[PDB]
Image (spheres, coloured by chain):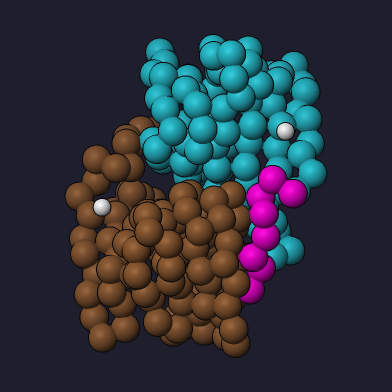
Chain colours: A cyan, B brown
Amino acid sequence: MILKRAYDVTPQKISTDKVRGVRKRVLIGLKDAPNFVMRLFTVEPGGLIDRHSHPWEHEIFVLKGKLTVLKEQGEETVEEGFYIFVEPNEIHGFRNDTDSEVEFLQLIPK
Amino acid sequence: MILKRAYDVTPQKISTDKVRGVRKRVLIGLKDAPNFVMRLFTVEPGGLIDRHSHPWEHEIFVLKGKLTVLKEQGEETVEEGFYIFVEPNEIHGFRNDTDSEVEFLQLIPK
Ligand SMILES: [Cl-]
Ligand SMILES: [Cl-]
């Protein structure tokens, strides 16, 4: 088995015309698993993932903080302990309006 | 999307000749997702999942507490923030030696 501390993984800052103030850690990656992968995202205060979509589903668990979820229309702010299923091709994004870091686990198929 | 509180899901107590003091919540189940599912397990103080295996892999994230992981040989106690990849057919189990509930997220393929 692989049994490791998530926060020991080196984060990558993500910075594009559509993403700001976000770090990503790959926990269980393509070389480790046969079917789906596990990542941990940290959203800084003011960070933003603009609405977008991919052709695969996402499964998310909110680990820390008040995550604002951008939906195909509108938004909803949720807290640690919420889970999210995002359909294939469903437009969605995220924002952190609070003064502390938000963390969420994200899993996607290979 | 599905956006819901994990702890609002009704738990099921699991009680067999190999499992004691464990509750299970299905968060994203077979009818919701195309490729893999997400469950949340709560291990009571003294709870125990005996060593066993399944022919699919598991991906686990420790949400709360000091989870003791039973390996194919021996054991290791780990804390919130650890992740686990369990290989197909790998013998493994879990125990809670502490005085408070332990929680972990578990995902498996369909
Ligand atoms: Cl970070
Ligand atoms: Cl419970």
Q: Is residue B37 visible?
A: no
Q: Is residue A42 visible?
A: yes
Q: Is residue A68 above or below residue B78?
A: above
The segment highlighted magenta reads: A1-8
The reply, left or right, for residue B63 in relation to residue B49 is right
In this view of the protein, which residue sits in the foreground, B67 or A16?
Answer: B67
Q: In which of the image's four quarters is ligand 1 placed?
A: top right
Q: Is residue A53 above or below residue B59?
A: above
Say how many tags the image has.
0
The reply, left or right, for residue A8 in relation to residue A57 is right
Which part of the image, by quadrant, shows the C terminus of chain B?
bottom left
Q: Quadrant of residue A48?
A: top right
Percent coordinates x, y for residue A55 in the rendering: 55, 40
Percent coordinates x, y for residue B39 in the rendering: 37, 56
Query: Which residue is painted at 57% across and 67% down in the image?
Result: B77
**Does the magenta portion include A63?**
no
**Does the magenta portion include A5?**
yes
Q: Quadrant of residue B16?
A: bottom left
Q: Quadrant of residue A77?
A: top left
Return the residue found at the far front: B99
Query: Which residue is painted at 67% across and 60% down in the image?
Result: A4
Which part of the image, by quadrant, shows the N terminus of chain B?
top left
Percent coordinates x, y for residue B102 in the rendering: 41, 56
Query: Which residue is painted at 63% across and 16% down in the image?
Result: A45
Percent coordinates x, y for residue A36 in the rendering: 57, 58
Query: Which residue is painted at 28% across and 68% down in the image?
Result: B21
